[PDB]
Image (cartoon, rainbow, N blue to C red; front, side, top):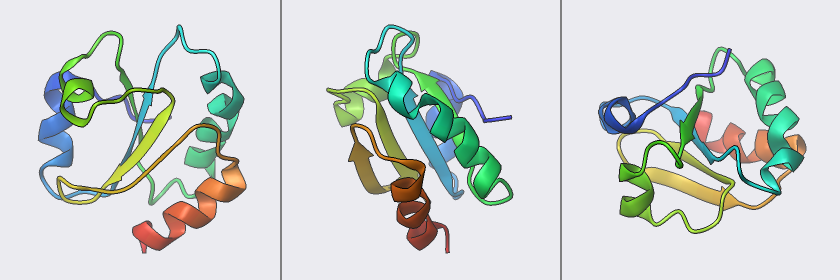
Amino acid sequence: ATMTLTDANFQQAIQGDKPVLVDFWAAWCGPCRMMAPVLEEFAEAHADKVTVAKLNVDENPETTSQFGIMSIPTLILFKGGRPVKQLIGYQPKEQLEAQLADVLQ
């Protein structure tokens, strides 16, 4: 199961001190379907390391205004209330797995 963050728990979650890859996506989005199954397989890949969380920026609009999430999908890794790496668009699971290997270690 992937994690599911939400406006209130979102910032209280990341700002503590915890590796969490927040996935910003929407059910009305077009090219988020491309990486849709790699993201759920991404939680199958590392699993005991990556918290692949899910914010609906449609439903929860507070953090999308802070960062300015202008084009979903948008993956951002937070380790201690600070996005170490923002990458967006379609990125294969192979691009993801090497990208997140650096920050998770």
